[PDB]
Image (spheres, rainbow, N blue to C red):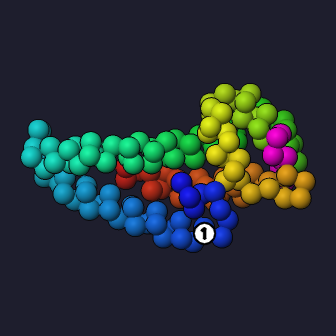
Amino acid sequence: MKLSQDSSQIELLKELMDLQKDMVVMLLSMLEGNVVNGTIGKQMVDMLVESSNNVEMILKFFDMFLKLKDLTSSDTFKEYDPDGKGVISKRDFHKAMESHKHYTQSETEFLLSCAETDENETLDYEEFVKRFHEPAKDIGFNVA
């Protein structure tokens, strides 16, 4: 939640996401050799229910930063910046968001807050997706 908004905490976010990936790896190692309806799985799901809200908001984070490639590759997004650099105004990005309708108002707001903007509110969409989508799906495959 907090580090995604700022811009001087990219390395800290990367380290944290690697730590989360290792934690999920350990959980899968616990789930190794588990029969159907096992005690280990029961404790799995009891822990998840205990930490339901955090898991829910992490999953929202993941859906949020994984739909980016789907929206970015769209011709509707390509229209707003046919140039290769694709520097797109913040409210131009907002109009693309609203046209796609895949995001909501809150998702749009938080994504715009996370997306750094230049003097003309123009953000390099390629750099943004590289920064917020490759760690995505990579930490997320373990969760899936």
Q: Quadrant of the C terminus?
A: top left
Hey, what amino acid is under mark 1?
Gln
Tell me which corner region of the image, top left, top right, bottom left or bottom right, holds residue 99: top right
Decide if residue 111 is on the left or right side of residue 44: right
Give residue 41's quadrant in the image. top left
Closer to the camera in the image, 120 or 72: 120
Give the x, y percent position of residue 26. 26, 62
Residue at x 48%, y 70% (from the top left corner): 15
Residue located beneath label 1 in the image: 9
Which image quarter holds the N terminus? bottom right
For this orientation, the residue located farthest to the right is 120
Q: Does the magenta stretch include residue 75?
A: no
Question: In the rendered view, does 51 fall on the left or right side of 15?
Answer: left
Q: Judge by depth and name the residue closer to the eye, 47 or 82.
A: 47
Query: Tag 1, which secondary structure?
Result: loop
Q: Please report the bounds of the magenta region as a residue range.
A: 84-92
Q: Residue at x 38, y 43 (%)?
A: 53
Q: With respect to residue 92, does 26 lie above or below?
A: below
Label 1: how many Cα within 10 Å (few below 14, some 14–19, many 20+): few
Residue 20 position in % (x across, y down): 39, 61
Q: Can residue 3 be seen in this view?
A: yes
Residue 66 visible in image: no
Seen in the picture, residue 28 relative to 94 is either above or below; the reply is below
139 or 104: nearer the eye?
Answer: 104
